[PDB]
Image 1 (cartoon, rainbow, N blue to C red):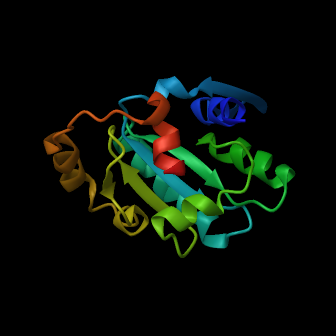
Image 2: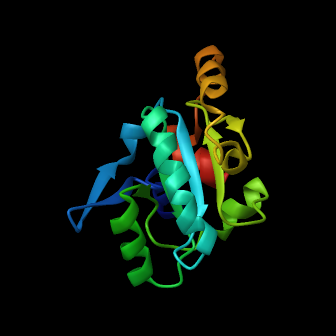
Image 3: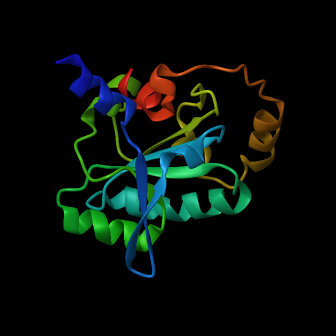
Length: 165
C-alpha cells in the first residue's frame, strides 16, 4: 500500500528536539525553511566531539543565523538526553542515522557540514574550518555572496530531500 508509505515520507522529520531548563521541547521543522544549517555529526562517547562543542559555541556567537542541528550516534537514549541538556542544540530524534553518513560519505566523528537554504553544501568539512578563530570574516563573505536559486523539494519537505534522497 503506497499511501501509508508516502504519507510517512511527506511527514518525515516533522519535529526537531532540544532541551531547555532540563525540559525536553520540540519545534516544528517548518521553522528551518530558508535557513542556513550546521549539521553536527557526533556522540557523547566521542571525546573530541565533546571538546568540539567549544568551537561550535564560538561559531554560534558569530553566526547566530546558522541553525545548528545535532545528528546523534549516542549509544543510549539516556546519553542522548544528557548530551542535549549540556549543549542546548537542536537535534534529530534519537534513532539510527547511518544512512545520512553514507549519503555524505562521513568517515569520522565529529563532522560538521554547512548547508545553504536550498540544501546545497556550502562547506563540506566545516569541522576543520572552525577549529581556529581565523575563519570568521571569510565565511561572512561566503554567506553574504551566495546566490540562492529556488529549489522545490519532494513533498515540499526540506529534510526529506536533505537526509533521504
